[PDB]
Amino acid sequence: AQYEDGKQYTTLEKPVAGAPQVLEFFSFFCPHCYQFEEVLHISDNVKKKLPEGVKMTKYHVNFMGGDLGKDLTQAWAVAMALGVEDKVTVPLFEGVQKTQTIRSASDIRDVFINAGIKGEEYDAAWNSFVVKSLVAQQEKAAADVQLRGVPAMFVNGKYQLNPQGMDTSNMDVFVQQYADTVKYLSEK
């Protein structure tokens, strides 16, 4: 076939019931994740090809960057709760990997402040039980799928994208193949 298990995707031998339709995992410490966000705009190009009626979910993971990794997962929960993902994603990536100005929870906080979220508003979210359960959800979804590597994308709790098995000679072509694969898996 043109799309084959173990080629553009792999199949989970242990499917995850009730899982989000399109589920993406990343880390602000993750170099390919930086590329995926800044250079390739994977999430976006996938959205552009997904059928409509499909929801897209993106979660942060703990297993990179130790204590700051966990802080970053709580901060992403804050970003999700306040709906400011699209204002903090880029400065977080660049603060961790490009300028290396993020070293503590306080520096993460500064990124939100500079993006215009209010101190009060951030610290309340940060400390809220709604954010605790949002952190819980991120961890649970990672736990549900055996996750030891990022970036990662899962479709309907049963298929996992496999970018190693796509051409990388051209970045535009890689993305399109990636997105088309998601659409195909979506329709499966």
Image (spheres, rainbow, N blue to C red):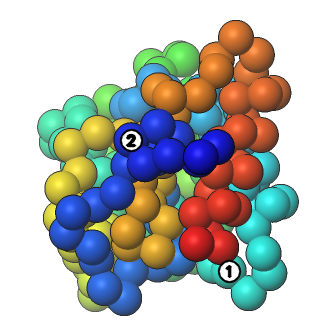
Residue receiving disc 1: 54
The answer to whether residue 138 is left or right of residue 65 is right
Residue 76 visible (yes or no): no
**For the residue carrying disc 2, how many other residues have a C-alpha within 10 Å: few (<14), some (14-19), or many (20+)?**
few
Rendered position, 179 above or below 79: above
Q: In what element is the residue under mark 2?
A: loop
Residue at the spot 70% in from the left edge and 11% down from the top edge: 169
Rendered position, 127 above or below 71: below
The label number, if any, that marks residue 6 in the structure image: 2
Query: Whole-percent x and y of residue 182?
Result: 63, 57
The answer to whether residue 187 is left or right of residue 68 is right
- Residue type of the residue flagged with mark 1: Val
Nearest the camera: 133 or 163? Answer: 163
Query: Whole-percent x and y of residue 149?
Result: 29, 39
Q: Quadrant of residue 128?
A: bottom left
Front of the two marks 1 and 2: 2
Nearest the camera: 46 or 184? Answer: 184
**For the residue carrying disc 1, how many other residues have a C-alpha within 10 Å: few (<14), some (14-19), or many (20+)?**
few
Nearest the camera: 20 or 117? Answer: 20
Nearest the camera: 97 or 169? Answer: 169
